[PDB]
Length: 115
Image 1: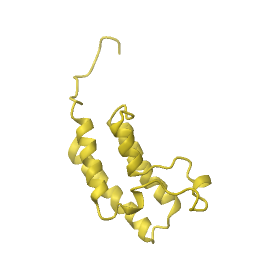
Image 2: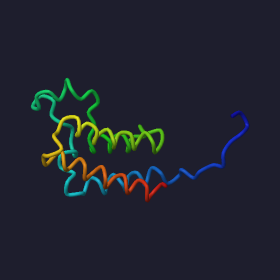
Image 3: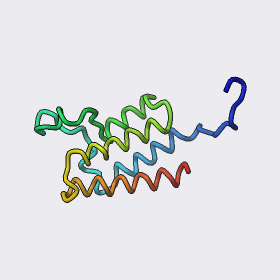
Image 4: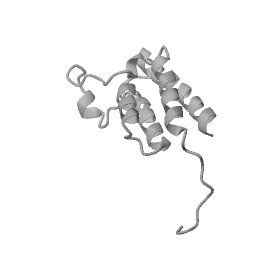
């Protein structure tokens, strides 16, 4: 509350560390469905169904341009990518499995880096 604060967590490295995590996601072999925005002209249903498209390249641009106020808003966009993927793709598909693998990969990096 006013003039009553928890001890100040050092957040000065968060930007760099989220960048490294994102690099590692970008270079994972199963990243291919998530590297670029889904092409809304060429993928019937996507525009109407997925209200908030997100992809790694869009996260990278947001990150590099100071559009994440904190590390939680960054994790929310990463998770959005996988939530979208689950919304549109059957679990038993290459893309569906890619999404599950990437989300696991992400969540471990996230825990190990920050928890």
